[PDB]
Image 1 (cartoon, rainbow over the protein chains, first blue to last red):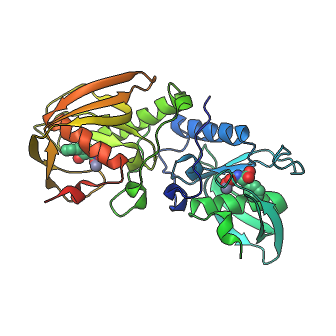
Image 2 (cartoon, rainbow over the protein chains, first blue to last red):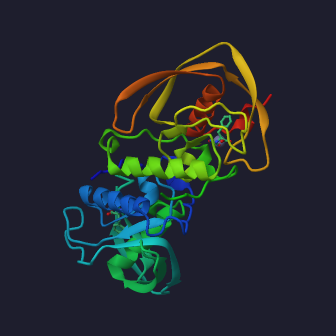
Length: 158
Length: 159
Ligand SMILES: O=C(NO)N[C@@H](Cc1ccccc1)C(=O)O
Ligand SMILES: O=C(NO)N[C@@H](Cc1ccccc1)C(=O)O
Ligand SMILES: [Zn+2]
Ligand SMILES: [Zn+2]
């Protein structure tokens, strides 16, 4: 097992548009290990999500993993989901405000997000999934996709 | 073994300074798998070297692997060397000029002046320190790959 260094605000890797994962990488040891290192890194830093660019990997892979922990004591439980090449298909016009932080901005803020999102993605095995999130998990999906598109949560404030 | 997508000139991932590999990564299955995918990619594309930023991984890992192949039919053959956190500690004042291509630059080769000899200190995948002297075409490969780690493409070194 490994815990990967996390890039911080100011580093240009967080400003890129991450590249999609290729068909060759689906169901590979390489991809399972990337996802495992990400997962371990998120857990060690009490994150509730992580995106590959945060660990210097400019690829479209995120994890969404709400759980109560010291950084988010009230966060709801979910089974962690690894999403390859996620795309938000629909954002609700209805919005919610919530406090976010970021492993890459060690500073928190209050951000407006869609209350609901519908997201398409591939599993690590290559299966195409479409699914709806609400509330805090929806916020995490939006924050992590933003990371894939070179956007930090501070740029969504004001 | 997986063959990975390769970034091309224009893509901003190739302009960054790649981050050093951290101590906890040394001798990790993570780092072994990265190197294996790099190596497979390089062989599948007939490269004689590869840098992690070329496969969208902004970390300081390179492979130097001169061998004759369809892209470089007269290259000398060496045993492939994977280098973690390579640092060039000496460049010779003597220069050689040679035609270089790049996995990241399609449809172009150019004449590039390189030091004829470089001394490079690096870590193995297990994390052991090694210092090696390279000459000639292997030396040009080391220099090209270290330039990839520093956000530089060979086109920026011409004339
Ligand atoms: O930086 C990351 N993700 O990029 N981790 C965030 C995820 C997050 C997203 C939205 C709201 C709250 C929290 C964190 O502080 O755990
Ligand atoms: O683009 C890469 N490496 O980044 N590979 C180059 C390596 C290289 C370096 C120097 C001289 C000739 C060839 C290639 O065309 O195989
Ligand atoms: Zn974040
Ligand atoms: Zn190159």
